[PDB]
Image: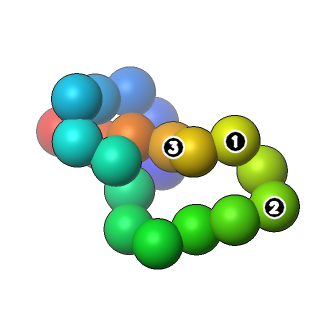
């Protein structure tokens, strides 16, 4: 739900998001 180098958890619809 922001920037990272680990994705947020399984998700669809929008672009893949990241955290920590």
Residue at 38 percent of width and 27 percent of height: 3
For the C terminus, the quadrant is: top left
Q: Relative to 13, is 15 above or below? A: above
Give the CA separation, mark 3 to mark 1.
6 Å
Q: Relative to 6, is 5 above or below? A: above
The reply to whether dot 2 and dot 1 touch (C-beta < 8 Å) is: no
Which numbered circle lies on residue 15? Answer: 1
Occupied quadrant, residue 11: bottom right
Give the CA separation, mark 2 to mark 1.
7 Å
Q: Position of residue 4 (x, y in %)?
A: 28, 29
Which numbered circle lies on residue 17? Answer: 3
Residue at 38 percent of width and 56 percent of height: 8
The reply to whether dot 3 and dot 1 touch (C-beta < 8 Å) is: yes
Residue at 45 percent of width and 36 percent of height: 2
Local secondary structure at mark 2: loop
Give the labeled residue for mark 2.
13
């Amino acid at each position: 739900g922001g920037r990272g180098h680990v994705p947020e958890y399984f998700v669809r619809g929008d672009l893949i998001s990241f955290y920590k």
